[PDB]
Amino acid sequence: HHHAMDTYKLVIVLNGTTFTYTTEAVDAATAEKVFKQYANDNGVDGEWTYADATKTFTVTE
């Protein structure tokens, strides 16, 4: 199923514990749509930052 994608990664830093979730997406606007859906579905409200060099979204709280 069409392989023209990057791997994107979500990092959620809590109290000394870190959860990450990494997934393929067509672009960063798309991976942010998936991740923000996942976050909300799990009890995660927080401050987000994206780093294009590593295709990583980082959420703290």
Image (cartoon, rainbow, N blue to C red):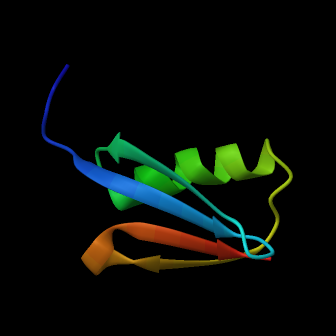
Left or right relative to 1: residue 29: right
Nearest the eye: 16 or 55: 16
Left or right relative to 43: residue 2: left
Q: Position of residue 5 (x, y in %)?
A: 20, 44
Q: Where is residue 31 in the image (x, y as percent from the top left)?
A: 44, 51
Q: Residue furthest top?
A: 1
Q: Which residue lies furthest to the right in this view?
A: 43
Left or right relative to 34: residue 60: right
Query: Looking at the figure, which quarter contains the C terminus?
Result: bottom right
Residue at left offset 65%, top offset 54%: 36
Residue at left offset 20%, top offset 19%: 1
Residue 13 vertical placement versus 36 (above, below): below
Residue 49 vertical placement versus 24 (above, below): below
Residue at left offset 74%, top offset 76%: 16
- Where residue 38 sits, quadrant-wise, is top right
- Where residue 41 sits, quadrant-wise, is top right
- Where residue 20 sits, quadrant-wise, is bottom right
Q: Where is residue 22 in the image (x, y as percent from the top left)?
A: 43, 49
Left or right relative to 21: residue 28: left
Counting labels gives: 0
